[PDB]
Image 1 (cartoon, rainbow, N blue to C red):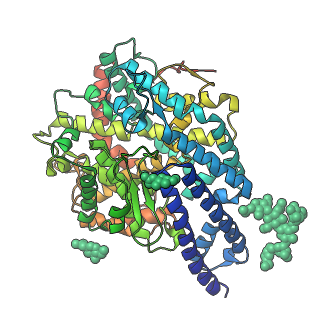
Image 2: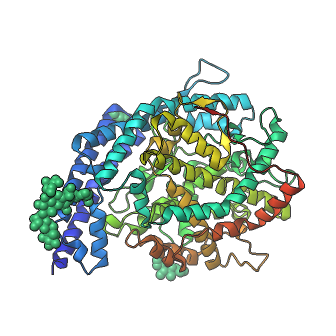
Image 3: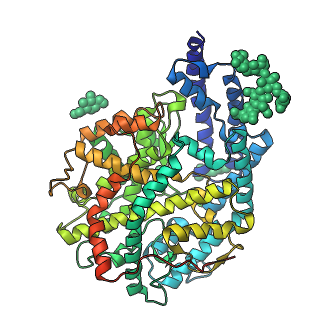
Length: 595
Ligand SMILES: *[C@@H]1O[C@H](CO)[C@@H](O[C@@H]2O[C@H](CO)[C@@H](O[C@@H]3O[C@H](CO[C@H]4O[C@H](CO)[C@@H](O)[C@H](O)[C@@H]4O)[C@@H](O)[C@H](O[C@H]4O[C@H](CO[C@@H]5O[C@H](CO)[C@@H](O)[C@H](O)[C@@H]5O)[C@@H](O)[C@H](O)[C@@H]4O)[C@@H]3O)[C@H](O)[C@H]2NC(C)=O)[C@H](O)[C@H]1NC(C)=O
Ligand SMILES: *[C@@H]1O[C@H](CO)[C@@H](O)[C@H](O)[C@H]1NC(C)=O
Ligand SMILES: *[C@@H]1O[C@H](CO)[C@@H](O)[C@H](O)[C@H]1NC(C)=O
Ligand SMILES: [Zn+2]
């Protein structure tokens, strides 16, 4: 009987929540686009206001006997409304948390270092100045300089703020009756065996990672010499072409299986053909529409920031996509550069935008991903296609390419330097934070606990000796910005399930046809692949994620089968190559974090 009035209650509340969240998002956008004390105050004050309203909402749900209802849909919506998160904190505690959070994100965004060759020039930012050096320099001491300068300023500088953040995050979780923030995050996956599932999948892929690790270390020894890289120790991370060693594709030119054969790097051809950020976004838009998916609305073009501002202002340059919870008001903020990697990043961010557009008709509480990993996967599925020789030849970015057996191994290896390498990295980001949230590590051991995990899982280490005098975790954007990271591990697994199925649907993959390998599938122009996306993305969070996966390809289980299938030709070649070259596998425990 009560369910009739409850349905009307939800309809109104959802629309109210969308409108109130719109206001919060606008202030958060203004701050990220233009970091000032006034914008910080505005963002945080509006968030405090919404938090207060959320408290009233959660209190009001107790007036409805929602757990007694017949409708699974009504119950699911009511359950979503009971989950306050940080808004469960007392007014003062919430205000303090907001203040600490903006302190950490603004610190990260404002980091500037001095030029290695010119101690007078001290306006080098991570994006683009420091990352330019990290990705391109092969001077190991230059690399170590920039690593140390960045981590000292982006990491160590916010230890006290990070400590208070952990305290209030924990207090918030417990007010929602989760054990810690780890459980609060994991609740988004609606599966009480989710951690164990990921341990199992990770364990299956781990041997391949160790083969890649071993081979890369071998190749780095030939380049830098044994004084810089040892055979038996963890790889010094500053040599891996990335500030966090999360992906190694930037060093592919020195570690590629067949150096005399083609290695795909289209950055130069993009510049030669006069690519701009605008063109890159237009091309991303073209890819989605070619699949019979939704075109970018005018608000996107009018309101997005697709180049780093040329005035003196501070901003968050870490790429992001934004939903404003109205109709068609969606935006990206990216400090775009004309590179191959950046072309993939454009497609990644546009994947978020497409998800927003696909579910914008859903009630507010359902206007989010089936789970956080789904949201991160969408654009990467297209990026996998964009990265293929097949696609890059179509758009004239890859010229005179001969796809023989050796070129194929080079391309598979290049992909693995991004996709397999990332897996242990992503797992450690949340394994670390979970252990702090759960109170499993004493504050006296917080820094070496981070590096111990990086060692154990990724077999990498800092370029210089660190200690508990340093605090390196917040040097990663997501750690300073309090963004859950497990979403990316989930993404990198499930995106291959989505890719394999989309490719099969597009007639682009057949396991028994040598002419249709998975690693050269291009889903561009495929309405059938697009249909599967529409079927899944339009659901938003209206159903538990296995139902969303089922809508795409009929499966209900997160599985490492597809990613293993993609890389199987590489696994076979690499295992043999490592044996042929007597390549040492595994690593001794690092000496780079002193207790
Ligand atoms: C996280 O877990 C917390 C517990 O660990 C939990 O906190 C509990 O929430 C309960 C509300 O669900 C609350 O229960 C109420 O307790 C009142 C008295 O408690 C006082 O004394 C306690 C000592 O004994 C103190 O420790 C407390 O601090 C309090 O000072 C009761 O008066 C109250 O009762 C009324 O409400 C119930 C409603 O229950 C339903 O009512 C409908 C009728 O519409 C029934 O049809 C239905 O079957 C059901 O019974 C009525 O039944 C009753 O007639 C009264 O009107 C109520 O029991 C509890 O006090 C509180 N703390 C503790 C320590 O237990 C948090 O809520 C959890 N947080 C989240 C976010 O989930
Ligand atoms: C940044 O914010 C300030 C006030 O905080 C505002 O006056 C200014 O217009 C903004 N700058 C830009 C470039 O938008
Ligand atoms: C394009 O999508 C519409 C609905 O969104 C669908 O009806 C149509 O079949 C699609 N086009 C093709 C060629 O499949
Ligand atoms: Zn993303």
